[PDB]
Length: 264
Ligand SMILES: [Cl-]
Ligand SMILES: [Cl-]
Ligand SMILES: [Cl-]
Ligand SMILES: [Mg+2]
Ligand SMILES: [Mg+2]
Image 1: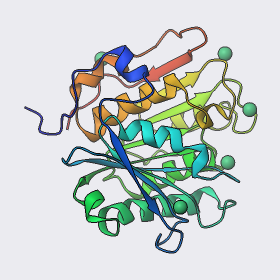
Image 2: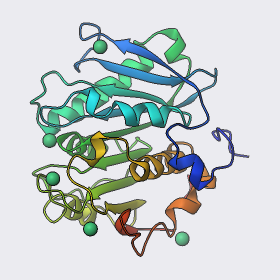
Image 3: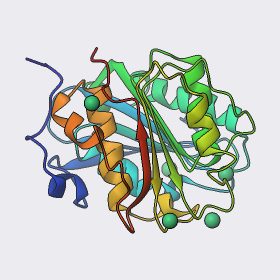
């Protein structure tokens, strides 16, 4: 059987709920102790086991407060998750890529033993909002050893991500006027290889700031993607293939994917 499975068999309601089946704890990461990023919060399951680990970045002028709900929710499904602050709130995407990587390595090596003992350091993922989503793409290109990448309403001036092989779910917002899907999220998705595991999910009725307030669709598909690719958990394939692929009014404007997904 797959040794990385955690939690009960999933349902729609379980994934749409405010929290998953794991109670969570928090560890503050001081700015002074945070090496190579601005600090942040680590959310982790109280139950002693090993889990995959995830770092999440905000965007320009943003703080961890704009992503905290999502890091806590993902951790409650069985992940160790750090929501970062950046060195300055104005850092550019390629700098945020570095900082996401530094945050992964902080969790693995420099957090409390309570946190470090809960991490499988071989199973890592990154996510981020807007310029933090651009940073997610850049880090994925640098680190094909990541198990998953989830850019949220991403922003980057580089439109060509044709080397990336990390399983990548891009979440766009139909009404985004700041990182429009026409010039950011869709070109990024279209440039990813056809031969990798990838998906594009466009939220319906959503602005650029949809990732900054609790969202049941972002939570559902972020957790299903992380389960499928960080944990190789094929109990979550059913949510992603074929996925919400004809739209779902007020939920999903469009969904594209390279289903079926190769299994590691
Ligand atoms: Cl941004
Ligand atoms: Cl917007
Ligand atoms: Cl399929
Ligand atoms: Mg702090
Ligand atoms: Mg729409």
